[PDB]
Length: 105
Image (cartoon, rainbow, N blue to C red; front, side, top):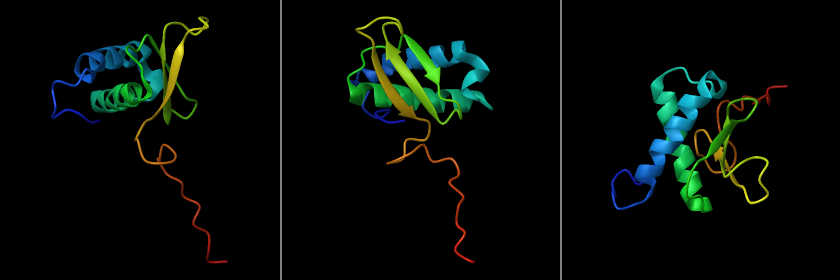
C-alpha cells in the first residue's frame, strides 16, 4: 500500500471500495486475516490509481490468489477497465514463493 502519508490523494476513498469488494469477494481471495484483506485492497487501489481506475466495481481473484483483477464497470461491458493487481506488489510477479533453487546437481 502507498499514499497513506499524503491524504489529498484520491486513493483514500477508493480504498474503501477495494476493501469492500474483497470483503464481498470473501474467501475467494484467500484471506487468512483481515490484514490480508486490507493488504490486497491496499495493493488493488494502488495499482488501480496508477493504471487509471476511478473505482473498483468488481474484483476477480486469480487462481492462486496471487493476483486480483480490479474491473471498473462490468465484466460483460465493453467499456470495462481492468487492472491486474499483484497481491504483494513486487516488480515482476506477485512474489509468494518461487522456490526453484536447484543448482546443487
